[PDB]
Length: 257
Ligand SMILES: [Co+2]
Image (cartoon, rainbow, N blue to C red; front, side, top):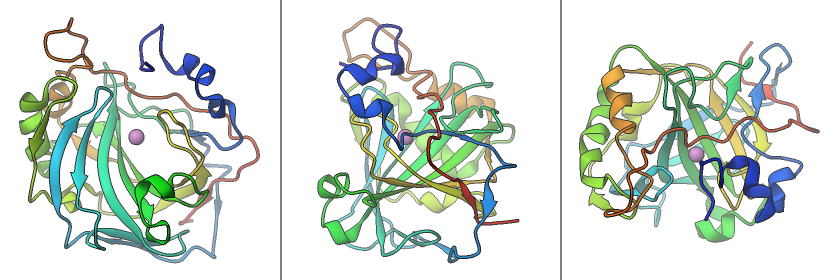
C-alpha cells in the first residue's frame, strides 16, 4: 500500500489516487506576504471542555488520538466555518530531523512537526459522509518547534511505547486537547484536502500562526514509533509528511493583520 518510502511515497500516490493532482490539494506553502486579511471571518471558537478521548492507535502512518464524536462534546465553530464541526481525532506529522516534519510551510519554512485536529461537519451525520463533501471537514493545524517541553503533550508521549507498531492501540481516556493549543488563535485558512490517501478535497484548513514548543526528548519519542507491524522488519516512523502542493486557483486568508 501507500506510505512515505521511496517506492511508495507522495510522488507515487497519484497512480492510485488521481485526485493527488487536483485543484485543491494540501498541504500548501503559506506565503505570508500574499495572504490577505479577511474582515468577513467570524471569531474562531474552540469548545473542547466536554471532550472525551477514548483511545490511541498506531495506524501505520501516524498515531491517532480518537474521541467520542457521537455528540457535540468537542467542537470547532466560527472563523471561516458555517455550522458545527466535531472533533474525531488528532494526529501529528513529523520529521527525522528538527528542520523538517511539517506539511504546511510558512514562507517555505518547515517546522519539526505539525498537529492536525480533525473535525467533521455535523450536517453530514458521520465522518464517512462528511469526507464526500466540499465542506465536510475542518482541520486545525498547529506547528511544532523544538524548544521547551509542552506539558500537555507528555501524557501522549508516555503512552507511545505501548503502541510501537502498526495496529496497536491503547486506552487513552481523559486527555484534554486544550493542552496542545498555543496562546493565540490567529490563523490562516484556505480550501484543501486530506493530506493522506484518499486525498479527498473536503477540508477547510485553519492553520494557526503561533507554533507550540515541544522538547527534544518529546520529539525523539515520536521518532521511536514504527511504521511496521510487530514481528516485521523495523522501520522507524519518521518523515510521515506530504510536501507542499500547488496552490492553483486559491487564495489564503488571514484572520489577523
Ligand atoms: Co494530518
